[PDB]
Length: 50
Length: 51
Image 1: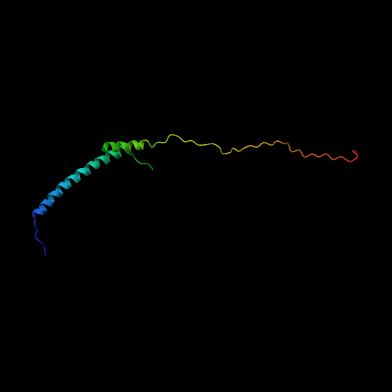
Image 2 (image 1 turned 180 degrees about the vertical axis):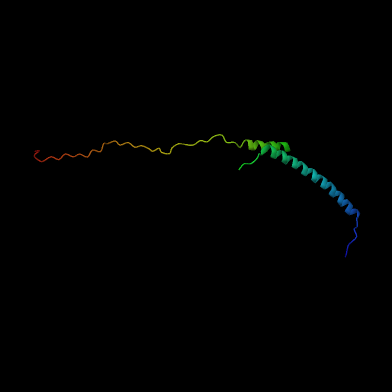
């Protein structure tokens, strides 16, 4: 009933561009740690038995 | 540096292997004693006149 128009100021555009750089670094860091974890598990652990 | 940490963890779990056990077998053993005198229980009873 009270839908508000969206205003895209220069501050909002600049804030989003900063977020894009942060997200890119975050995904890159996560991918590296996944690779490190997968190598560590394969070398140091085996299957379980009852 | 990441590889150094991964190789260190793997070597740590490879070093967690037992070698042997050492213990003492002493149950059942007791200390002896030495008796210096034979316990004879003899007395000599003789009359006054020796009869």
